[PDB]
Image 1 (tube, rainbow, N blue to C red):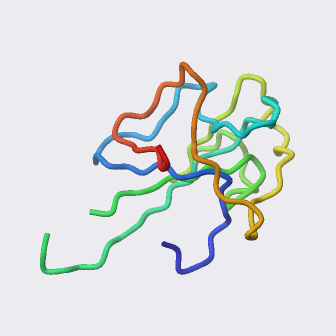
Image 2 (image 1 turned 90 degrees about the vertical axis):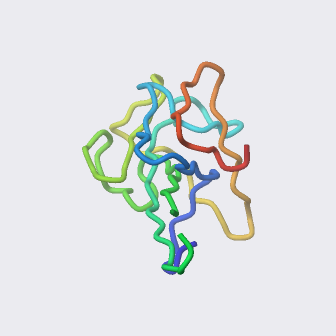
Length: 133
């Protein structure tokens, strides 16, 4: 949950479930599939949402990453590929990362989040669960 309204991702999140596992994708992979969007627009970044749980007297919330097309979201102004903590840049080999993706953000009650899926051959990061799968 967010107590400051977040920028909404077009896709479901990827949740870390095993600590110590790195969130990564092979270069050229990692952009979720949106029906009808050209491969040239497949460029953006996954943004880490650190979650914190409240102390109980029992015993854990691991981060959840959300995808934003290049030029949108919390790091809309950053340069593709720049080393920034909590930002993992990804792009199809058809994408030109000097230009923002031609994509408008999601919402209102106008669109639900697209369940995150990747093309056949995509190497999935071990230790992460794709929400909606």
